[PDB]
Image (cartoon, rainbow, N blue to C red):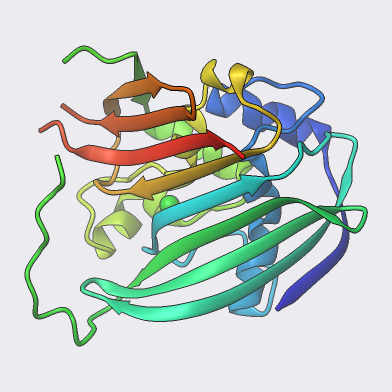
Amino acid sequence: TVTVEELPIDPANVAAYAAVTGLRYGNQVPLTYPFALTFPSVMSLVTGFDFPFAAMGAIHTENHITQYRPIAVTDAVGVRVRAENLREHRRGLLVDLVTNVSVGNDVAWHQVTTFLHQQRTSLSGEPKPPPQKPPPAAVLRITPAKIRRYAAVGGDHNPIHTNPIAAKLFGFPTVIAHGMFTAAAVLANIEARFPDAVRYSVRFAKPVLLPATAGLYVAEGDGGWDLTLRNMKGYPHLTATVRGL
Ligand SMILES: [Cl-]
């Protein structure tokens, strides 16, 4: 467990984040923003010192955010993080990083982030699953330079997103986008209609090799939104759901 009593929010950092992700800057932080805000506290738990990087080569596989109420740019926040549920995967060791962000003594925003830390495991002899696979609602175009900018703003400088040598050392043929860049970028416009209490579940699949041109599909429903971002192969970079609580 790591604990941070009172963490102020810099409105400039929110603005800069909203600008880079293409999201709206206003009185409420964007739904995904407390990922960036808390991340250096998250990695101080694994490292013991403040460290603003996911472990080099780590792969973000899943993220579940439950927002009970919006967090104001003017709020200061209580932060508590914990690590749990180590388990083996074919391509490494998954761990869950569970974050509680409070305003007053109430929990406004909760997150389960699962990172895959690459390494051989006893499941590594075992075959590659297959995937689970028209004109899109929008097209995301993502450059190395947008992702160098995202690194500065979103609390994670893991150099597999910015330096090709680092990427290559960890199995990637070019630099790749951060998972949470893309998780934030897909919310553009759509976010205007979110209720204040909302859950956002993201599953990450094919790495977003840069430069990337990627088609975004959005089905709106009574419950909320189903999102899929893909590369036209046409396999998924992510699939996700937004649901009003
Ligand atoms: Cl990532």
